Length: 141
Length: 211
Length: 144
Image 1: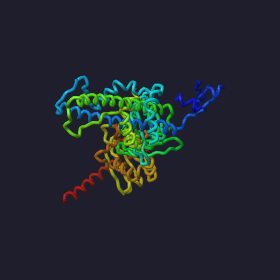
Image 2: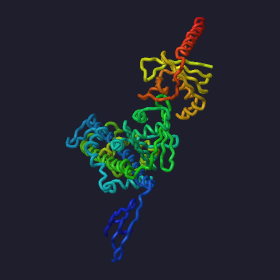
Image 3: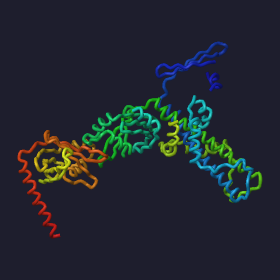
Image 4: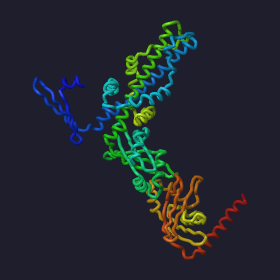
């Protein structure tokens, strides 16, 4: 079961009976057919808090701190290009001039233009690819 | 009442100072009734109420202190002393307020929220917020990389720095995570009492729910 | 014993000023006799110790603080913030009174009155006391 699931995280099927989820495995262990059913109840509010709500909230806070630290980083790069143009008495190839960063306008452009797809829950797919190394870290912490 | 639920999905979370702990609460009030979702960051609780329940429960809690339902609701919209018990899983939330120069009582009869509303009001929004915040990190990291291409053009031809304290190191995202994870993550991911959540994330909460 | 005459308006009757007379033994908290009149007719009734305890327990407040609200309503003790409102059928003789805030009137209590049989006479007594009482506080004032 471990060696079957590790690469994938054979065939599977998913059936609900009242509150309970059954996950069915058809595969082969040796050349012979292997069958399993997982029998899952609804997770308790403890588990959902510990595995989902709390870590997901702790990730959003830490990511908000990332955005803050990247905004102070951005402004510190804007003081630096200013110090070149304004007093460091020089120019560039022009094709690379960035706009001065302001997090108010960064957020308003982000939230009109990019939010519709960015917060897409979808298949949960992109959460497992983009966010897990943060998830493991937040949970440890 | 369907519009009360719809308002609720898109209301932000407030933070409540009990004597006993704190709570997080999102509420939507109209003249029609209210809907409320509460959490202590371990559990979640729900109530929805129309004006029929308002004038009955207020006449019980406040025997002779008459009003139309909508005037009580209007005062709760102002939002006092908070206490609670979990009795079974009624988080009964007991609220003492001042209105008309009279002490007032409301008790919220909050049952364990359904897993479906926990999904719609927390997990899905909170996930959607983490993905959106990560796209903001991604766009600040492209913006930081773009400002380095710009600043490297200066470093490539003439253009010395004057103020000997304006230097930026070249932005690199893996190492910015590495330092954050040791120096910043302990504090920043701490749930605490949920005041960090209500203080800085409610705009994104409101946006992601409306998306 | 103490009494206190107070001027009020019924919501039934905007332009008619009514007079409430309350009469009790120094603590209003110990219960009281109450009279209403409108210059044309009169009505009377009574309230008691355990009723006022129960009625403050009824609103979850400290007794004495609730007696405060009763002084202020019934005895003209209204602070600058306080507006009070009076309701009465003369037919049923059901009284009730209230305070106005929150864009509402809030009930503060209810009485069974009875229509009084000698209207002009309790009126006569009532206003003679008033002529006298003005005159007593006047004589103290002159000296000061």
